[PDB]
Structure formats: C-alpha cells, structure tokens
Amino acid sequence: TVTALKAGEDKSIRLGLFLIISGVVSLFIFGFCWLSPALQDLQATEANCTVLSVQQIGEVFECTFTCGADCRGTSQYPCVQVYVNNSESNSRALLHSDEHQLLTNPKCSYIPPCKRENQKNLESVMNWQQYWKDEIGSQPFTCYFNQHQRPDDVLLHRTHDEIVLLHCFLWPLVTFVVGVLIVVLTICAKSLAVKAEAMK
Amino acid sequence: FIWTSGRTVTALKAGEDKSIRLGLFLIISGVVSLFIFGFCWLSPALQDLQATEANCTVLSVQQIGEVFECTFTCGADCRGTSQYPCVQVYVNNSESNSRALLHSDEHQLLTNPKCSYIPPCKRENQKNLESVMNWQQYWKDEIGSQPFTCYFNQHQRPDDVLLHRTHDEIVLLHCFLWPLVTFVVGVLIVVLTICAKSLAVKAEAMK
Amino acid sequence: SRGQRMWWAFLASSMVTFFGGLFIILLWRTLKYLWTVCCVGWMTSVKDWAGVMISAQTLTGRVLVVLVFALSIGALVIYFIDSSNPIESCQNFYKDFTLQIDMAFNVFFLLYFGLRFIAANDKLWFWLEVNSVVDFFTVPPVFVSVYLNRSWLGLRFLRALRLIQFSEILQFLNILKTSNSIKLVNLLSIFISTWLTAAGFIHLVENSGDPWENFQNNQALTYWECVYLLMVTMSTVGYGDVYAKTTLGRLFMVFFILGGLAMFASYVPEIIELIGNRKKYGGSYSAVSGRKHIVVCGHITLESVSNFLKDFLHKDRDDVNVEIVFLHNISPNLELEALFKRHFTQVEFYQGSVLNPHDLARVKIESADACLILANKYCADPDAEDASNIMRVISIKNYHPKIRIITQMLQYHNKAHLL
Amino acid sequence: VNLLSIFISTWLTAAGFIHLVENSGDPWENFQNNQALTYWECVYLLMVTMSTVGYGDVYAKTTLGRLFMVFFILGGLAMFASYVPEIIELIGNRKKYGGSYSAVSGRKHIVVCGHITLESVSNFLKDFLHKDRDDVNVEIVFLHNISPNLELEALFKRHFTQVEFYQGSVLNPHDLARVKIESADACLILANKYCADPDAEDASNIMRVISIKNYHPKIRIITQMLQYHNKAHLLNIPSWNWKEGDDAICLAELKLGFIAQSCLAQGLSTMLANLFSMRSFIKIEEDTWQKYYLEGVSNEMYTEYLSSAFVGLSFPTVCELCFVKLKLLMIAIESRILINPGNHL
Amino acid sequence: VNLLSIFISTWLTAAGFIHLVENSGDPWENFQNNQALTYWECVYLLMVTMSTVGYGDVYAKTTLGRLFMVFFILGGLAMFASYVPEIIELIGNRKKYGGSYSAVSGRKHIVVCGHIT
Ligand SMILES: CC(C)CCC[C@@H](C)[C@H]1CC[C@H]2[C@@H]3CC=C4C[C@@H](O)CC[C@]4(C)[C@H]3CC[C@]12C
Ligand SMILES: CC(C)CCC[C@@H](C)[C@H]1CC[C@H]2[C@@H]3CC=C4C[C@@H](O)CC[C@]4(C)[C@H]3CC[C@]12C
Ligand SMILES: [Ca+2]
Ligand SMILES: [K+]
Ligand SMILES: [K+]
Ligand SMILES: [K+]
Ligand SMILES: [Mg+2]
Ligand SMILES: [Mg+2]
C-alpha cells in the first residue's frame, strides 16, 4: 500500500543517514585537526631528569597583566634560565616547564603569573628560582624531551591533556552509532508494521 | 557585481493616509531606537552604576623612577611623543580597607594604570615634568587629610580607585528622552489624523 | 563556585529530551502493533479543543497566539541581554530577575508545546517539526539552569527560529490575507531568523575555540560583531576587518557561504520588489470655485493627448480657464509624463477605469462640464472598439445621467445603438 | 552529481596548486619569498575568492601565486556563480502535499476535485460549512494536480481542523488510494463554468468519473455538467447509479429550466436559486424592498422524515398542522417524488 | 536623467550622513571613538561598498556608523546592481550604419535592397 506513517518514517531515515554521514565527516575533520598536535606530543620521549645549573641573564623581558575588562599593563620580570640532564642527550639542555612558556619566551625557563607590581613578579621569580636552585643533585624529575626537533629544550608537562583529545573522538563515534540505531529501528518499524497489518 | 549582476472617498484621503504611515514609522522608530540605545548603554550603565561610592584618604605617594610617553598635538597633524614622570598614589576606602592605586578619571586607568595621573601633554618635557610635580605636591600633603568622596568596584577592580564617574548622566538621559518623544509625537500624529478622518465624515453628513 | 564546567548537562537535557522522546514514540509503534501479532470519543474532544486553541478560532485562542508572538520576541531579547555576559557562570535564582522572567516565558512555551502535541494528527510528524525541535533545544536547558543555579550561553541562539512562525500567527489572526503581503512577511521572517541564528552559532564557536587546540585559539567577538560579520559575508562585501579565526568557525563559514549567498541574492531583490510600488496617480481631483473642468478618457496615448491639447489649448480661442482631467487605466510612460509636466497648471492625470463608479467619483464626474471619449481609429476590429466606447458611455451615464458626453464612433450602425 | 563532483574536484585541485606554489617561492627571488600556508588555509582562501567575499586575512603573496590567482579569478568566479545556484536549485524541492489522508473512527469524509481554485474553494466552503446546517463533522479532502498558491494555502490554514489538501491526479489509482476513496462518503467534481470549450470540459469531467468508478464502483459521485448531451453519455457508465445518489447537476438543463418556469410565473427563478444558497436572516431597519426580500432569502429547502402522528393523514391537513402550529412551510412534495399530491394517493 | 539623478543624489546624501556620524562618535562612548574622515573619503567608501568591492582600507568604525552601513548595504547594493547596468544600457547604442553615401566623379554606383541576407 502506502500508509499515513510513511512521511515521518522516511524523514527518520534521512535523519539517521545525516547522522551517519556527520559522524564519519566529523571523524575525518577531527582526524586532520588533531594529526599534527597528537604526533608532536606523542613523539616526545619520557625521561628521568636532574638539575645541573641555574642563573639569571642580567636582563629583563616584559609580560602583560590584565585587570579584567580591557587592560595591557606591560611589566618587566627577571629572566631565569635552568639547565637539566636527560637520558637521551646526557648533555646541557634548557628547562622550560610547560609548552606554552617555550612558545612565548624560550630564552627563560619560567614566566611568572603577570601582575600590576614589578616587585610581585620579581619576588615570584625569586620564590620559584630558590626551588630549582637547591634541586641540584636531588632525586630525578620525570620530564619530557624531543630529540627529533628540540634537542636543547626540556618540558615538565604535556602539550595537551588526553581528556579533550578523547572527547573529540568519542562524540563522532556516538553520533554515528545513534544514526545507525535510528536507521535500524525505522526500517524495523516499516518492515514489521506490514507483517502486523497482513496478520490483523 | 554580486551574483553576476542582474539576471465616499474624498480628496484629502491621500495626505491623511500618508500622515498615518509617518505616525506609524515614528512609533516604530521610537521603539526600535529605544532598544538600540538600550543595548548600547547596557554594558556602560552597569559598569558605572555597579561602582560603589566611598569616603577615601591618601596613605602613600611615590615616583617609580621610570617614564612613560604621552603625545601632544599642535592642531593639524602632529605626534610629538614626549616623556613624563610616572607618579603613583595609594588610598584607603570603606570596602577593602587596604592599599589600592588611585587613578583619578576612568580614561587615565584605561590608558596607563601603572601611574595615578597623566598630565595635559605638551611640546616641552619641562612643562609635563613641572605639571606632574605641581600635581604631586597636592596629593603628597593630603596624607591624613579630611576624606575625599571616591569610587570603587569590588567585583572587578579591587586595587584601582577613581575620583570621577565614567560618564555624565546628562548624555545618558538625552539618549533615552528623544526616543520617547519620537514615540509620543508619532502617537499624536496617528490620533489627530484618525480624529480628522472620523470627524470630517460627521461634519459632511451634518452639512 | 568557579573552576567547574557543566555545559554538557544543558546540552544533554536537550539531546535526551528530543531523542529519548522520539524513541518512546517509535518503540510505541513497535509494541502496539506487535501485541496484536503476539496475542464521538472523549480523546477526540480534547484534540478538538486543543486544535481550536492552537488556531485563533476563539477569543481565548486569539489571546494565546498574541502571547506566543510577544513572548517569542521577549525570549529572543533575553538572549541578546545574556550574550554580553560570560559563556558559563553562576547566578542565584532568587536574585537575578532576568532568570525569573526567562522561567515564566519558558513555562508558557512548555504549555503551548503541550497544546500543539495534543492537537497533532501524527505524533511522529509533529515531533520532527522545526517548531518542536526549537522547543527541545531551548525549553529543557532553562529548567536545568534553575535547578543547577547556573547559566550557559549554549544553543540559546535557536530562539531566533521562533520568528519563522510569525506569518502563520498573523494568518490565523486574519491580519495577513493578500498574496504579496504573505510573501513579504515569509521572506522577511526567514531572512532575519536565518541571519540571527547563524550569527549565534558563529558567536558560540568563535568564543569557545577548537577542542583539539585545547580551546586556546578562541576570539573575543560580541554577538553584534557576529551579526555584522554575517551581513558583510552574505552581501559578498567581505571587508576582512573581522572574520572567523577558529577551524570550527571557518568550517561553518564555508557552509554559510554556500547557503547564505544564495539566500541573500534571491531574497533581497524580492523583498525590495514587494515594497515601494506606490501608485503615483491614485488620489482624486479637487474642483475650485468659478473654474470648470472636463474629463477625457478612452484612447489616451502620447500622439492622441498631444494632438488633443494642441487644438484644445490653442491661442485663437478666448480665455479658456477649463481644466482638463485625464482618466486612463494604464500608467503613462516617461514621454507622456513629460507632456503632462509641460501642462502643469491646466492638465491633471488620474489612473483608473471608466467602468468603475469609484473612479468616476474620484474624477468628480457629477461636476464636470463634459466628458470626452477618444476612439482608437486604427484598431484591428471597429466593432470591438465601438462596443467598448458604448460601454464607457453607459457607465458614465449610469453614474450621472445629466453629464454631456462627446464621443467618437467608427461605424454608423453602432451610432444607432448609442441613442 | 556532475555539478558537485566538478565543483569539489576543481576547488580541491586548485587549492593544492596554490599550496605548492606559495610554500615554494619564486625561483628568481631564490625561493626566499615563500609563505607558510597549510592546505586547509588554501582551501579556505579559494572559497573566499570564488564567492568574491575576499577578506584579505589570507591572500597569495608570491608572484607565481598571484599569477595563478588571476587565472583562477577568471575561471573560478564563473564556475561558482553558475554552479552554486544550480546545485541549490536541484536540492530541497520537497513536495509539500505528498503523503495521504488518515481516516478516524466515527468521522466521515468527502473528496473534492476538478476545478480547484481560490474562488471555487472559498464559495464551496461558505455553503458547505454554514452554521444553518446541523453538527457537520464531515472532513473535506481536496485532490488537485497543481500546487496551491499563497492565497489558497492561507484559505486552508483558516480551515485547519476541517479541510485537508493533497496534490495528485484523479486519473491515477495511486492518488485515489492516497485520498482513501474506498471509505469516502461521496466524491464531488467541480466544473470550470467559464471554459473556452464546454465539450472539452465535460469530456474531462467524464474522464474523472470513469476513473473514480473504476477504482471503486460503490462511491457516490456528485458532478457538474455544462452540456445536456454529455449528461446522456454519463449514464452509459455501468456502475453509475442515479437511483442511489449519483448526481449530475447539468447547468444547461437547470438554467434553461429555471428560465422556462419563470415564463409561467415571473421571479420563480429567483426564489429557487435563493432556496439552495445557505444564508442567515440579515436585519435592516429602514422600510425598503430589501427588508422584506432579506426575510425571504433567509429560507432554504430541507429534507426530513415524517411518520409519528402523520402516517395515514391527508396531505393538506398535514401541511396545515405544521404550517399553522409548527411554524414551518410544509412539504411541497411527499410514496415517490410527488409535488403537492392533493386528497388522494 | 531619472536614474542618474537618483543614483548620484542617494550616493552623495548617504556619504554626508556617514561623514557626520563617523566624525562625531557614539554618544554613549562619550564621543571618544570618532574617526577623522573627509567627505570625499566617505564618498569613496560608499562607492567601494555599493559595488561590493569592499577593500577595507577605509570602513566605518563607530557603532552608529556600522549601524547605518548595515541599512546602506541592504538598500544601496540593490540600487547599484539595478541602476548601473541600465544607465550603461541607455548610453552608447550609437547607430553604426547611419550617415550617407558620397559619390565620386567618373564612378557610378548602384543601390541594392529588398531581401538582404
Ligand atoms: C527533560 C530534561 C529536563 C532532562 C534531560 C536530562 C538532564 C536533565 C540530565 C542529564 C545530565 C544530568 C546532570 C549531570 C550531573 C549534574 C551535576 C550535579 O551536581 C547536579 C545535577 C546535574 C546537573 C544533572 C542534572 C540532570 C541532567 C542535566
Ligand atoms: C513524550 C515523548 C517522550 C513520547 C510521546 C508519547 C509516545 C511514546 C506515545 C504516546 C501517544 C502515542 C501516539 C498516539 C497515537 C498515534 C497515532 C498513530 O497514527 C501513529 C502513532 C501515534 C503517534 C502514537 C505513537 C506513540 C505515542 C506518541
Ligand atoms: Ca437560512
Ligand atoms: K578586504
Ligand atoms: K563581491
Ligand atoms: K573584499
Ligand atoms: Mg489642477
Ligand atoms: Mg484533518
């Protein structure tokens, strides 16, 4: 026959196919977006690491504080640099703590939380330095290194958390599975309703 | 171009119906401009009226031993970038009861929050130097004086203090007065036109 | 209470409401029928009452749809106010009066959705209507907002899709009737709704950056800056003062460029074509004391009018104060409008038909000294021309028996019918 | 699929050529003037160029790249401006009035077809849905091969709970099945009275009835006919049965008959036409011929059964009783169709 | 003359309104966000907008100005795209085969007409 329910059921097939396509397409989009970040992080080695020298270069860089709502606040801070041992190079390389720090100023080992007062960023860098200054010959850190591209830079932290990576690939797969269930339940309803209609 | 370019009745009825179109356009323009000024003033009016008013007293003053640059204008196309002393002033207030930097007017804070003042910028370094000295020698002596009345914002600026408001209430008032007047004028045009149409037919029957 | 995010709870409340319901519908279609293989009515009176409420059929129903129109604007204005605030934050339900108003509006939209659901013939067709989808993506997240004592500027922008139903509401209210006016309101509603909705999606996506990029590449654009960006894109101007910088944003802009350009280039010419066609030669003649006038009609053409005015306004006549009023159903071309501008103080033209007594009243035939009817001498059929001019005279004489008529006739046997 | 394939292929290929050329600079410039653009940044650049938006956030900086962009501007703009309107025109033409009617228990429906037009539908609904009738629960289903215009769609929105429209042809048994003709109480066929050729119109309406009767012999059909000789062809259809309510309203027969009866009594054609039009009593206070005419116009002719206390009485007595005390103008006829029978039979 | 007058008048009038609005900034912003544009710079801006070229060398920076530019983009693009093709179509249709024949002494000529194909 034809039936009254055909319009809603065929629209339900169009939705289920659009979700299958959108699941696969967003999987490729996130695939290319995460390709360079995921390789650039997961190619970094994990190593045991120990401090071997510390110093200030006798010169200052500028950070920018924010008040909240439209401030620049450009303010000087001491440039402290720290050199560390690692299992691959076994030689002098500059510690940068987090990746962001390296990307924003690789000549210093730290950037303080920038503030309206020069004195607070000075004492913050002193309060940070007096830790790594005493860690000379201490029990090893665990730290990250990249011999293929960064033979003289060292990191304390990863470039991204695996949670945000996982969520970007979970919801495309869930979208695809939901689309498949909509297609299957709709085709099941269409093909079973005609058996019930003949059996009535 | 865009998209590959192109692919009874009475004699007075015309003027009166055009007068209705005008009165409705003024009603619509009154309401629409009220919403436009509403969104334009929303963030400024909240950001100013959320600031508290307080009694305030000076507690320290100093120059940071370093200089910022202002720009003078001659009139007609000058840059004139010129150094001035950075003086900073700290003040008491009733909410924080603690050290916060005075900035005088809001503009000053927005242009250089590390100093408490900016002089009227001039072609001579000596005149902006002595202007900052002549300003500083006031707030330098106001230590322990009778309170100012001053403005503060605990929700967003816990370490900045202002002597002045961010806008005057007169320009705010005018932006909401003339939309309302426009709407009222539009309503009077509609009412007087409908009154003329509906009364003229009574006079024409009574003649 | 900062340092925690809850955006997924707002989004899940919409996704679970829409799909959860949809599966209940379907599972109900697979269980009702399967039971029969394994093993006037009261409901219709409720469905009749709900249908009679959903349309403006009764006083109550017409009050309801006027509230739907007003609260659709109100709920969109609440989203405009909220768009200036942080993307996620805490706000107490007993302190922030905007969230109380947003509650009262969304409680009304829940009840209106309930009436629509009751009135519908097929629940599955209804559940997949655009107006139902907009409710699942905008009603549940407000109840989550009040329960969590928090806000997220998530899919709120979908409120702008309620403007699409304004032409339907105005058709129910018997306000829209004419085809051009319904077209105009349809085109304006779809254009404005699409523009404001698409501006809200790019707003959300640019203010919350690419997830892979760990959200670090976001751009601080206001909602109005996104509305301006989409207009500059749709029109194809594309200044590049502002543009989408995130990958998700650039992605969306590729699909908006494919859909929105065709929408602007199709709709803007047509909305301008449905407006401003103001009839220039409407209105009517005003007679002045001591000055008579004549009405001229029939074959009004540039050569006929210029020949007529040369003989009528000749200087070998005496002080002819007689004003000449032309009545013709076709708008004059630029040449004939220019001929009337050369006679500005003694000729007037009004568009209309000699067969309509309203147009005869507009031209003041009851006070005209005479009516003159010009014939087409060079017509393809003299009998159809004479029969047309016979019609004109019976119309003019029907409106006013006493007016003097002067008329050209082509064939003599048609002159006998005339008398 | 041809337009989509050529559009996407050209765009992705041209993005790859500008990618290569911008990442490896002008040879003369000793390759020093290269620009670090990703492939996706080149895909975005070409879309922003094809559409003519041209933001200039990103643009080709090398001479080879600018060179290529001149030829891409000459070819790719014409490609976008031609293809994008046409790909959008080949999509989304979703037929709004497909689907079919679902009947509900205890509520009958009728199918209306033929000359479906704004004036014909609005005239039909004014007489059919009149309040001088009784509780008319009958649903009205229109079947017509042309999509309704905005005015006629608006007329259907004003009747949302009692009118449904489906696009289709009376000559197609699938469309007759979609409109549930096998359960319709009657089918009504409207004629174009003002057609250029009455014989082609009548022959078209004859086709409609043989199609409806072919799909279901037992449905009641009501149809307008223009010419009387075409009505004689109509009753040669084997399942056409005027004894059970198949009605041919012949306009030439009834028109010339009204006129003929007005030759025996002037104005009879006026009151007969007023008795079938549904109209309320309009009230006018001014003493005019209109106040007494409008009172007469308020009447219509109605059928009813009579038996309790009227079986076996004389026809005049029966007329007197219900005229005098039931205050209604009695039986003009009737047993069979006997007009004003008298004292016998 | 109608198309030229309406085009030029609209362009020069709209350039004057954006001139005034950009040189005297947003009232809420305490008039501080004004831009020093000359009138001719506003005439150039509106032509670059109407044509849809939109270089963005100059553009409206104030909120009132951006506001006006949204309504000018909705009205002025349709005006330019309709009027410019038609003004160009009403010009330059110069009849190429007007003029007349000049005879020369001692050389005769014939005239050919009718079915010229
Ligand atoms: C029909 C709608 C309202 C229900 C949709 C499902 C929604 C409401 C579900 C899905 C996920 C759930 C949320 C996830 C977890 C939390 C955090 C908790 O600290 C408060 C409750 C809250 C916020 C839940 C509330 C209910 C919730 C939002
Ligand atoms: C509220 C959400 C979650 C589900 C709504 C209730 C669902 C599960 C139930 C309640 C009433 C049921 C509907 C009532 C009757 C009909 C009409 C029939 O011709 C199609 C199925 C349909 C449409 C039923 C489908 C299942 C149904 C919609
Ligand atoms: Ca009656
Ligand atoms: K540009
Ligand atoms: K362009
Ligand atoms: K551009
Ligand atoms: Mg005059
Ligand atoms: Mg129905």
Image (cartoon, coloured by chain):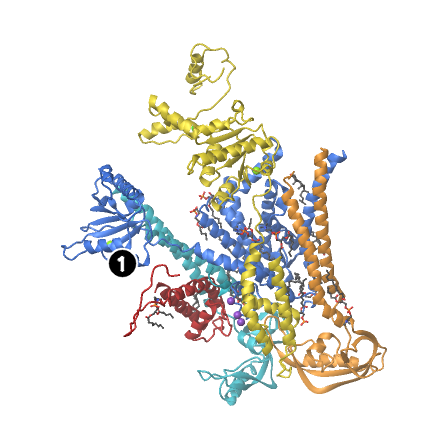
Chain colours: A orange, B cyan, C blue, D yellow, E red
Q: Residue E13 falls in which quadrant of the image?
A: bottom left
Residue C77 in the image: x percent, y percent? Answer: 54, 57
Q: Please report, as a chain letter, where disc 1 is located.
A: C
User: Looking at the picture, which amino acid does disc 1 mark?
Assistant: Leu
Above/below status of D24 relative to B34: below
Say whether residue C417 is left or right of residue E17: left
Residue A131 in the image: x percent, y percent? Answer: 79, 79
The residue positioned 62% from the left and 41% from the top of the image is: C122
Q: How many labels does the image show?
A: 1
Quadrant location of the C terminus of chain A in the rendered image: top right
Say whether residue D290 is left or right of residue B27: left
Q: Which of C47 and D13 is in front in this view?
A: D13
Would you say residue C219 is visible in this rendering? no
Q: Nearer the viewer, residue C386 or A129?
A: C386
Would you say residue A46 is visible in this rendering? yes
Most distant residue in the top direction: D344
Residue to which mark 1 is pinned? C339
Image quarter where ligand 3 lies: top left
SS for dot 1? helix
Some atom of ligand 7 lies within 8 Å of the CB belonging to the residue at label 1: no
Say whether residue D310 is left or right of residue C318: right
Quadrant location of the N terminus of chain A in the rendered image: top right
Dot 1 crowding, Cα within 10 Å, few <14, some 14–19, many 20+ = some
Q: Nearer the viewer, residue B183 or B120?
A: B183
Residue C123 in the image: x percent, y percent? Answer: 63, 42
Residue D140 in the image: x percent, y percent? Answer: 53, 35
Above/below status of A59 relative to C243: below
The residue positioned 56% from the left and 43% from the top of the image is: D97
